[PDB]
Amino acid sequence: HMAGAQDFVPHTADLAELAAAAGECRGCGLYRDATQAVFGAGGRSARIMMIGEQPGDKEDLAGLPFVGPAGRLLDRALEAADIDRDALYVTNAVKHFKFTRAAGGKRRIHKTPSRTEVVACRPWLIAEMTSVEPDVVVLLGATAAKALLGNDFRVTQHRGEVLHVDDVPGDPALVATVHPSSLLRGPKEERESAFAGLVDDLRVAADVR
Ligand code: SF4
């Protein structure tokens, strides 16, 4: 248990115990500056798991995943797909906010977790997957997609595709889609196109049998 977060992950599938243990994780350096660990949220009967990159500024203080503008956009997209809450477990590839500030900024600015951090934190993701046994996993953005599909995976090339990789416990369906935060910037028309495609991918996931 010498690698990354491995020794911090208890031998239990209980999400409450997992979240408590993740609160004490020192498996990479990100715990130092962040406020708290942000574990995933939902229950183990969920059939759809969603994985973002990391808790953001709001998530870091809320102690819950997907609470910012990007979570609100995600809510809009789940609505437009016909996805119910009880079906969902939502979490992040890295579970401590990695960040910096810029003078005059209105928020703390997220920084991209390195591959080393993603791999160090992945024992938690594996624990969550084995705990939840989802039918499908939605990977929201490149960091999360690469966490499970390989450092060379390209989200832009596999949109709407149902993927299956044989080193993911329980062989769930996998669907890689856009980083919802990316849909906050830019021309309305392209944000609307992007939103429709995210809904497309969520429907694809929700229809996995
Ligand atoms: S990011 Fe993941 S591995 Fe690094 S300290 Fe936080 S929980 Fe542990």
Image (cartoon, rainbow, N blue to C red):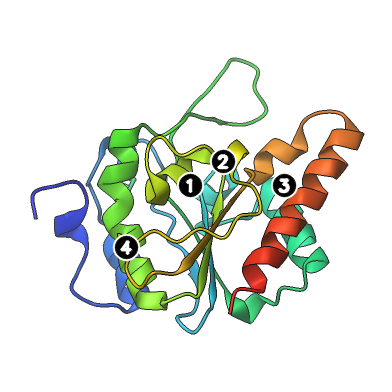
With respect to residue 11, does 165 lie above or below? Answer: above
Q: Of the residues under marks 4 and 3, which one precedes in the sequence?
A: 3
Q: Secondary structure at mark 1?
A: helix
- Tell me the number on the disc at residue 126: 4
Is the CB atom of the residue marked by disc 1 within 8 angstroms of ligand 1's nearest atom? no
Q: Of the residues under marks 2 and 4, which one precedes in the sequence?
A: 4
Q: Point out the image quarter for the C terminus.
A: bottom right
Q: Of the residues under marks 2 and 1, which one precedes in the sequence?
A: 1
Work out how far the residue at label 4 is from the one at label 3, CA to CA, in angstroms: 27 Å
Depth-wise, is mark 3 or mark 1 nearer the camera? 1
* Residue at horizontal 66 percent and vertical 54 percent from the top: 160
Q: Of the residues under marks 3 and 1, which one precedes in the sequence?
A: 3
At which x and y percent is residue 44?
45, 81
Q: Determine the image quadrant of residue 186.
A: top right
Decide which of 156, 191 is in the foreground and name it: 156
- Tell me the number on the disc at residue 155: 2
With respect to residue 163, does 180 lie above or below? Answer: above
Amino acid, disc 2: Val
Residue 207 relative to residue 123: left or right: right
Amino acid, disc 4: Ile
Around disc 4, counting alpha carbons within 10 Å, would you say few (fewer than 14), some (14 to 19), or many (20 or more)? some
Quickly name the residue at label 3.
Answer: 69
